[PDB]
Amino acid sequence: MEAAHSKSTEECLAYFGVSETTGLTPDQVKRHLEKYGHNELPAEEGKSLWELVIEQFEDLLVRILLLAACISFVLAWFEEGEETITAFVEPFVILLILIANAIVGVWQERNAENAIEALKEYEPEMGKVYRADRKSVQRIKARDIVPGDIVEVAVGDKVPADIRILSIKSTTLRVDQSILTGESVSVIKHTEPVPDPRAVNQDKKNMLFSGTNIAAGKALGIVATTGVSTEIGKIRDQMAATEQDKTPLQQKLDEFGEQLSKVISLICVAVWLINIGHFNDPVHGGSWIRGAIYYFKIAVALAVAAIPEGLPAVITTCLALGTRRMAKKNAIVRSLPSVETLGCTSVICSDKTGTLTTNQMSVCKMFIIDKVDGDFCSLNEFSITGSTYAPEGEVLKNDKPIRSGQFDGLVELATICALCNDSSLDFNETKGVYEKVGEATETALTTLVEKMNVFNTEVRNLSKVERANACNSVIRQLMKKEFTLEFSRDRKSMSVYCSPAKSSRAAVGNKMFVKGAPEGVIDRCNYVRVGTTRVPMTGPVKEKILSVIKEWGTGRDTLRCLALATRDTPPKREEMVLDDSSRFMEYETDLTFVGVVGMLDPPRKEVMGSIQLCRDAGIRVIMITGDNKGTAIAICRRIGIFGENEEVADRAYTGREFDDLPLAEQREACRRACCFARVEPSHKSKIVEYLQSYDEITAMTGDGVNDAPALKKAEIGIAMGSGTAVAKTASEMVLADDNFSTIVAAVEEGRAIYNNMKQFIRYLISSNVGEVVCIFLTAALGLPEALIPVQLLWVNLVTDGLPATALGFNPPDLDIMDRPPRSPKEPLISGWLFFRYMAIGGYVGAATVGAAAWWFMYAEDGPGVTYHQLTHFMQCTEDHPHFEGLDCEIFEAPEPMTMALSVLVTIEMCNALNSLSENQSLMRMPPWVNIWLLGSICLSMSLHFLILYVDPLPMIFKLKALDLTQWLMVLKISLPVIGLDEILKFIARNYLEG
Ligand SMILES: C/C=C(/C)C(=O)O[C@H]1C(C)=C2[C@H]([C@@H]1OC(=O)CCCCCCC)[C@@](C)(OC(C)=O)C[C@H](OC(=O)CCC)[C@@]1(O)[C@H]2OC(=O)[C@@]1(C)O
Ligand SMILES: Nc1ncnc2c1ncn2[C@@H]1O[C@H](COP(=O)(O)OP(=O)(O)OP(=O)(O)O)[C@H]2OC3(O[C@H]21)C([N+](=O)[O-])=CC(=[N+]([O-])O)C=C3[N+](=O)[O-]
Ligand SMILES: [Cl-]
Ligand SMILES: [K+]
Ligand SMILES: [Mg+2]
Ligand SMILES: [Mg+2]
């Protein structure tokens, strides 16, 4: 029964046809269970090994390397070489990479906790129903509750299903529905119908939504919906439905994968066309099982030359150290790939209560009477600092700290605030922070009289645990609380009867202490207290009081004003009926006005500056709240979203107002409006989707259950450390310190990290370019020598993995936060950069061929002085008279591959020096600006010497030769490549402008 809020109690009972006094019958429970199912949110399967791993293998590049590993087993089958039969282990290496990388992804998926499971902690095990079987209430399992059941709830109870209230047994029914509205304030429900069919949960003041707990009271209702059909079930559906898109940079890697598969697949067959040298090479033989293997010997090699193996390892470690660096800023990152995505955030959506504000009700202003001389009436107004329940702060008058005990009116104001109060203030030693005990509204009064200290009580050397209620107890011991007249809806106020308990009994006179909504209380105040004295209430006086109260209720500050009064001559205790709550308003008559307090959930001190910093960084901040519109706007003015006097007309909408706009006017309404109030949990997710429709990377910040959908729909979800568990589970990052400025710091770190990522990404990709060009030249000139598939792995994994990781520690740009947010879909390589890498790739790629070619043509220690016919080395066995003065094994000497690998590694170190910047020269950018860069080059070169000057590793590859005749020649290209890139870099820095 969805329209249950708009139908009367009798109409709701008539829908299911059950008498309010008696419960459903077993037949009805059978049928309603076979129709509506059980009352439980469905679980989620989440993970599957057999399918998660294969999903990790679904990527394209891993399909290329995987397709190359088996071929590498085929090359490994070959008994031809075996001496190099033992070197058959390259595929396993090629294999052990994939496996390893795969596992890392699985590990990233290992931490994915079930957020629906966290949402299921808000459904209770047992529930209380009345039924036909038994006159006495039945405590059953809440999952067996079907619609139509008569359900009972009491204090502390968790509501099991969405329930229309039939009769409230207590004076009031206060429910904490922060699960859906994000507000710790407890709403006062009723049984009247709510005619609006499209009312939001905040307006359904006659319903009891599943997952919310009863703050105080006892009531009876009939169940409307169960299971997924409840309002929390909408949250579950929206949390299982919103799939997370791939990281923008990850999308770049994927399309790079596609084009890479195209280019590899086209080159491998493109070699078949240039087969002028394959028409008739052997003396009689042709293409058989031995001959065709060449077309694969290049293939796998070409693959390992194109695939940047180890890039996921480098980005994984880089993002890991980013997580460690932000961890010192109290920013716990749950998803590694999200860090990058935080840099390019264009819009930040944010909750208010608990996120932008402290979620701790604080009394800002207060006023008492000063002088009453005829029509004139002056007031004493005070402001109170402190934005938390902790008794920290002082009272001020005209921006000057003043002791409260000097004003006789403030003493009585604190006396009313302390006695007429059911709440206490506790100090959590485990969390190390003061927590409210009771309602937030009254707790604000408790901490208020803690801040005031009207009797000048020594509280400096007090323990932090006893500091919580130090002054409240002082006031409690002065007047004994006989009984309390509880809050009722008819009079919108509550009162307390107190006796002196003084030295001489109650001869000083009993007094009644009343607090409540302003108009209803002031209308019953026939007297006004001026310090110690009492004067009759008049027109001009109450017009001044109501004037100031109206000035505080609206405008810049939007405080919740409570009026406080006493009764100097209350009636006798033996003539007050305490059962009938409607009579209490007569008991609270003939009052004496005292003062007024103003409450507000104040913002965190760290927020406003953060909003200015995002504004400076081109990031717009949007507030999305379940709280009232006036309150959210008044907070926006303090935060810096709106001006102190800015007219907010078309810039702030409510969920009901938002839904009334055409879908177009909503999608465009998210571009201008910066504040959204009184919204349902679905509305936040809808706004996030709308902002993402503009291809804008948006981030959501929250702390409650109602923020869970948005937190999933946003590209980056940021949860508060003091927030709910379900909000943390559906987020990519947590702020343990609850500070809002660490978001700004986190964005800065993300941008700097990406700026450092383009560097080593371009480095590895360029090395792959040179390798591809080299394998192509060696393939077209018939010289598979000087390169092997095994070594290209170690080069792209170890000797290049270290400098690439070192590039992650480059100093960030100075004016990095004065620039607007980065474009989402923009290439890492542009035309000029693509031209630069296209030239240097063929240059350094031809270097590696020139190593072997030079070792054979112009060399004093290279016996293979062939001079000509070097390209036709395969004929050496069938045309031995052609190749005299040498052995058939000299073609595969250790020096060609040692020199090719040498110029490769050195060109890669110098190229890693070129990767320190894109448009900045090396003369103005000293290489020692990054100690980790030169350190990684020193360690990669040291590991290269370890490859050469050892016994195992050479057996796979080749043997090293002397240096008096070898390193002198590696400098033909190992060093002038820096000059090439230096000219190419000098051109665009000056020729581009003018
Ligand atoms: C040589 C090595 C490989 C892996 C390769 O083919 O990379 C190309 C390639 C797929 C791209 C190109 C490479 O283009 C070339 O190779 C130039 C001509 C072909 C030479 C072959 C014979 C001499 C990248 C490498 O060119 C450079 C950097 O010079 C940059 C970039 O990729 C990036 O955005 C950088 C990494 C994400 C992509 O053009 C990309 O394709 C796209 O769709 C892009 C837009 O992405
Ligand atoms: N944004 C807020 N900031 C501060 N307080 C809020 C806020 N919203 C609600 N409250 C308090 O919570 C109680 C719940 O009332 P409820 O009907 O949910 O809200 P509203 O009255 O604002 O109506 P609305 O939903 O906006 O139409 C009110 O009762 C009282 O103070 C109010 C109240 N009053 O409103 O007059 C009197 C009172 N005593 O004791 O006199 C005690 C309250 N209380 O404990 O919550
Ligand atoms: Cl509102
Ligand atoms: K998310
Ligand atoms: Mg919140
Ligand atoms: Mg309200």
Image (cartoon, grey):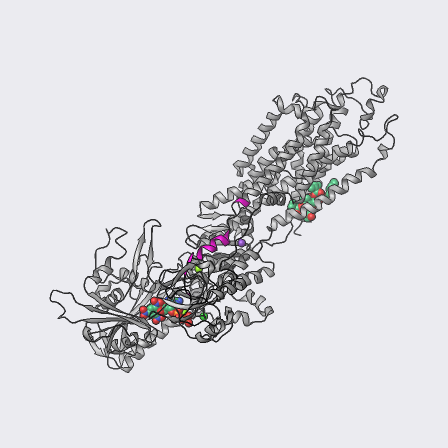
Q: Quadrant of residue 263?
A: top right
Q: Which residues are magenta?
A: 109-133
**971 or 330, which lies in front?**
330
**222 or 122, which lies in front?**
222
Give the image location of residue 924, x and y in percent: 57, 41
Give the image location of residue 515, x and y in percent: 29, 71
Say whether residue 307 is magenta: no
Give the image location of residue 922, x and y in percent: 59, 39
Question: Can you name the residue that lies furthest to the top here?
Answer: 885
Residue 517 vs 422, above or below: the answer is: below
Question: Can you name the residue that lies furthest to the left here?
Answer: 504
Q: Quadrant of residue 438?
A: bottom left
Residue 589 vs 383, above or below: the answer is: below
**899 or 225, which lies in front?**
225
Give the image location of residue 729, x and y in percent: 48, 52
Residue 644 shows up from this direction = no
Q: Residue at x 79, y 34 (%)?
A: 780
Residue 505 shows up from this direction = yes
Say whether residue 117 is magenta: yes
- Total marks shown come to 0
Q: Quadrant of residue 587?
A: bottom left
- Ligand 6 visible in quadrant: bottom left
